[PDB]
Image (cartoon, rainbow, N blue to C red; front, top):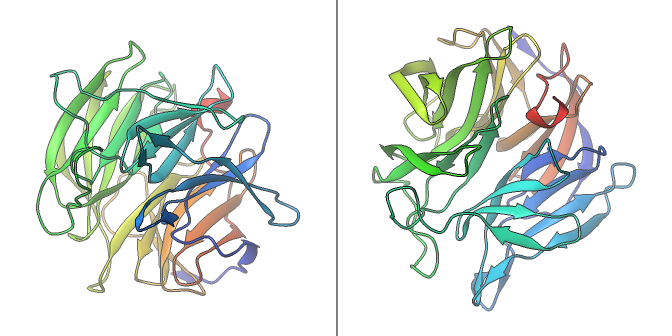
Length: 305
């Protein structure tokens, strides 16, 4: 089955718009990773007024003269602060006043961080992170689009930054499937160009096993799975960049059980508005943000627990 809901524009003129997130007060944010100054990265985290779509710069992260490429966001639970995956700087924690901190320059083995693109909290508070880029600044920016050097990290509640896997070709969206009792059960990771969704079984903080292909992304277009989010029934909605569709997987994966046709070819990121059926989706055909109504509420995010 294929559904065609009405998409309503939220805001426009945001190059590479991604990282949609709601904070603990219901303020909406997205990131503009392609902002430059003199050919060098100067990406921005924006706050969006939901009534007018007007954009307000919250944070323009730069460290020692190297500008960031903010790319994916999650809201914290114990504090109204945003965990931001940055393709040049690693993991940031951003405050609403625009100040920010770099969380880990090196991983638990002492090795320089790779640039990060998506992240997802489990309900225990560990942050699972995809890192499709090469070494963080001051190294030259590189991207694992053709070669298998993308990595997967877990930033645990004890404050450890643990590389839990590597050798992905452009890992993208990440999400955590929880049991009904709240325990983390599977980690889902998009590997975009291979048209695969991978899963592992979560055994504990930064402990994953049983790596397997969890789902297959339709199509042969350039692109594949980008962002993803679970609904309250643990159906996984996955933006299939390049396909004009968002794929809907059942909780056990496999093939899509349904698809959502989009009025654009390039959906990227998606995020539920808490306590509603409204999905916000970003897309790079119009460099815009849209919303549409899903069949049921989103899965509760860590920040709402």
